[PDB]
Image (tube, grey):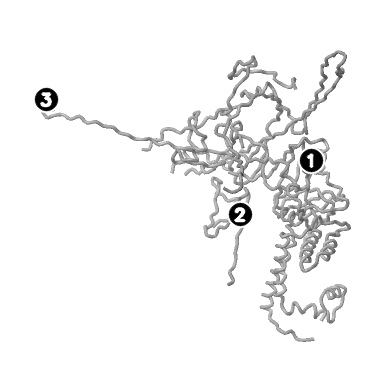
Amino acid sequence: HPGFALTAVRTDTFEVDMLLYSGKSCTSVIINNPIVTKEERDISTTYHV
Amino acid sequence: FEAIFGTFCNRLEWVYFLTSGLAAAAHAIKFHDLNKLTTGKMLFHVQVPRVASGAGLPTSRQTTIMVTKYSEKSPITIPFELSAACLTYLRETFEGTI
Amino acid sequence: RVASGAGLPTSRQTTIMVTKYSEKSPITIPFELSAACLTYLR
Amino acid sequence: MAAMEANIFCTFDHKLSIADVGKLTKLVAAVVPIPQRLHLIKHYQLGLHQFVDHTRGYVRLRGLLRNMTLTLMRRVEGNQILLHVPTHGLLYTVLNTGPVTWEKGDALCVLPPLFHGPLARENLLTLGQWELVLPWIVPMPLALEINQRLLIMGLFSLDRSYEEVKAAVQQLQTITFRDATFTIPDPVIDQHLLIDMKTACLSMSMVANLASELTMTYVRKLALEDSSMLLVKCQELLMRLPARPQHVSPDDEIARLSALFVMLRQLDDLIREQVVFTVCDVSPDNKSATCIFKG
Amino acid sequence: MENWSALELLPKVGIPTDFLTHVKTSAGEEMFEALRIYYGDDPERYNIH
Amino acid sequence: LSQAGAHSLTPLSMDVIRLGEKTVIMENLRRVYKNTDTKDPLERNVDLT
Amino acid sequence: LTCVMRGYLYNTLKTEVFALMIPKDMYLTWEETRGRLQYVYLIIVYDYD
């Protein structure tokens, strides 16, 4: 035995589930209509919303 | 013969925001000019009840409180893409064959 | 797919095709008859 | 699966004030860099401030900016900015960020910003210990002089003592260009510049070795019977100490001079930046110009 | 080896299928034989011959 | 904001419990994500040292 | 032969994209992680010893 009494620390990660409670209309969300944007190339065209 | 019995597709379980119970926690409003605004703020004004007290103890006082709250930001996006051949067949029909 | 915020990547058009194959298991059982019983049957 | 986006939206998440979106509107048609391309990105990745570190080496910032991608700003609106990537050869409009004056018919380069005057203009969206530091668009001679002076200062740092280096650095830190003057911030010597020094000195010794007898003797021969201010300056720069040419061989000479031509090209590429813009007629107020995007 | 073009082009029956695991894992871990996992839109279904 | 909406109303079914006369709704968000690329954010990691 | 000098590489009807093939011994990479966009170059080097 050397002249030490070193202490160890280690952390664990758990896979766990959650349950979440809220009241009626805690936060109000305001949104606009989806907006379409376009990009063109010869092989394929693409869209973003 | 190999006898393909059937070609099976998928029908998605459709979900809409107002259909879910999570909407009960929410309050959903549309605002067509939304992208223009910088921030949305709300103001609160509160005054407190006070209790009269007997001599010997210092008396309570009036108070006034103002509180301000601010709006969040969280845009979302989704891409979908198509190959030019599908566009060509959507637009152009040629030789009329089946 | 499901939307996500800025910075994070997003999933694309994705399709999966899968196949199922049949399994075979023929069954059998014999029954044997004698010549005298066959002649009576005739 | 993947698709290369061309229209880029940047969204802020700090609770901006009216002055912030006001200053954003002033920045319309400027150029901003992005490290990665997506449809929607956070403001933290936009601008050059993310890269600054306490060492503040200018060569590091130049090298980092060389790798980045360049985009233009369009249709500024509330907390959502649209950035359009340029396509090679198209005609674009741009508003210059820095104070350097432009001229028509020349080329432009991208450089990290410089110390100019009182250092007044840093009002660009300073928020939450983050700021929108834009790169500079400057004409070719100023950029070439900046690169030249950094490299020359680095070379001079060797074989010299500390105080001689300090005097030389304090001299080289300044630049003059088209009635304007600018100062280079934090031009500290670093290992990034040492790589450039090594390759430049190798190329310079190669051009020294490849030079033929006639090429070397040309200047000394011409000084014999010609005279002009250019010639006297050139001779004054050189050290001080007819006949038939010692050897004549156009084939070997042309091969040698072609090799020396390649070596000179390699030496020159050290200071030449990527030629991003070729310019057209500019608004007389010098604020905005029409340019073609190249490279 | 399977005629995937036929599966794309031919009409098909709608079902509310329910994979036990997340479906991308089932494709990733070769539960089925003869898969095809093309991303995006693949125009190869059109070259009828 | 109280004037901004909720003018039209439709019925739909969900589960409820009676506790402390604060009747509340329960919904399991497994169906909304199911097969998508993003994981359900209620399935969380917890850490202890 | 027909050949493209500024192009996306495709069949006439664009029914399918055409790939470009490089022999394995010549192929070289100088980074372990790849950004979603990367360029490809032709490289010639000489041994003078």
Amino acid tagged 3: Tyr
The correct choice, above or below, for D148 with respect to D207 in the image is above
**SS type, badge 2:** loop
Image position of G43 (left or right of B35): left
3D distance between C-alphas at marks 2 and 1 = 36 Å
Q: Quadrant of residue B52?
A: top right
The correct choice, above or below, for A32 with respect to F8 in the image is below
**Which quadrant: the C terminus of chain G?**
bottom right
Please rate how many residues cluster around mark 2, counting C-alpha atoms within 10 Å: few if below 14, some from 14 to 19, many from 20.
Answer: few
Residue D127, label in figure = 1
3D distance between C-alphas at marks 2 and 3 = 91 Å
The correct choice, above or below, for B88 with respect to C27 in the image is below
x then y, percent, for residue E6: 47, 38
Residue at 54%, 45% (x, y): give it.
Answer: G15
Mark 3 belongs to which subunit? C
Residue topped by disc 3: C40
**Which quadrant: the N terminus of chain G?**
bottom right
Residue at 79%, 58% (x, y): give it.
Answer: D187
Task: Pick whichever, C14 or D127, lies toward us.
Answer: D127
Marks 1 and 3 belong to one chain: no
Amino acid tagged 1: Leu
